[PDB]
Length: 77
Image: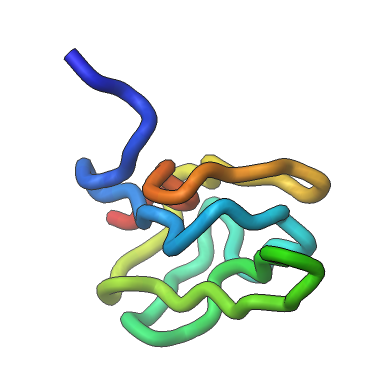
């Protein structure tokens, strides 16, 4: 009982920001630290780095899309 947050492999967002551009895609491999997506929180470009090494199995964020703090941004495998 309680949905709207990452934890099951999904990378939780640090805060409520707007999706500007996506770097990683379903198929590309990412590393713990490499940028995966850019978020514009409070008219400020924020770089989103992967929490751990893995691969993008599903992108839970698209351009011109608003995300909530904690909400799963991208699923890593």
